[PDB]
Amino acid sequence: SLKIDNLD
Amino acid sequence: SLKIDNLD
Amino acid sequence: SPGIWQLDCTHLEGKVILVAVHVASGYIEAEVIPAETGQETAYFLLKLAGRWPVKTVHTDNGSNFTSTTVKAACWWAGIKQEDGIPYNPQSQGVIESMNKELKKIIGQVRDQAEHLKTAVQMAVFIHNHKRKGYSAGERIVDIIATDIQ
Amino acid sequence: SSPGIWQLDCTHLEGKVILVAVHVASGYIEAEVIPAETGQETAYFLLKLAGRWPVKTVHTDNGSNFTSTTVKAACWWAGIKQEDGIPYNPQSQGVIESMNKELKKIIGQVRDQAEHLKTAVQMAVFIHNHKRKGYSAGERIVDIIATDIQ
Ligand SMILES: [Cl-]
Ligand SMILES: [Cl-]
Ligand SMILES: [Cl-]
Image (cartoon, rainbow over all chains, first blue to last red; front, side, top):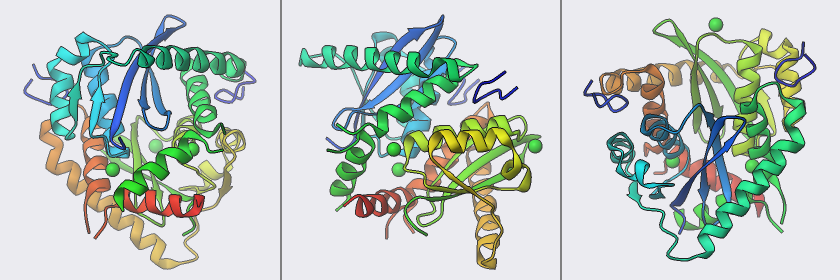
């Protein structure tokens, strides 16, 4: 999802 | 429960 | 004093951020929990005292001061549990200002993290590395090393 | 054995995973219990560690955490050089094994004082780090980094 903790 | 993390 | 820490509890996004500040350096550790309970506070203090030489903790309110679980953790880990009464009125102000700083930091990183707990650890990292000249993480290491010697 | 070097180590107990970071020059440790080792859990753990100590290099515990792009993204974020954990020094292999066996021994000594394994692990981190063998590991890490700051 484009987050450091959720790259997806 | 007598335990440090559950005094019950 | 090298061993003295202050607990502080602040709210964001319907959740609770529990913070321990090392008073002499301003260095902090923090975690996100769904609500402040004596069991969460006790576990947080056990974590803190295994990582730094925690001699005294000023608790953040009367419920954690009273809590027998918190007192049991402070017994286990060799911590003197004290109240957090600001006999020095400066103490109220300093904590309020740190909560406002941390919240500011958290807003600056918030979009980089899906979960609030990540944003809070990014804020701990920025807070502890910030040069004001030394950082809080440098100051805490210097203070305790001086004390060990 | 420079002040900023840490090693990750993953061990199992009670159907659960204990992730450990060791500061190689002092033996000081931080640890947490997780249900399984995933790159997201390892990445979060390293972000925690690097906000609390000046972490320059981490030798990862296996090739999946070395490969994990989430672990690489946390190491990028926190300014950490991510390295493999190959024991080019065979001593290194032995020192980890024997720390896992010591931690597990300590966990058995406290296990009955805690309902949850995560409590028992934090009590073992506390005992490990305070044990004088003479300085404790928590004393050695502070001295090492303070000397480096100066
Ligand atoms: Cl696993
Ligand atoms: Cl730091
Ligand atoms: Cl310690």
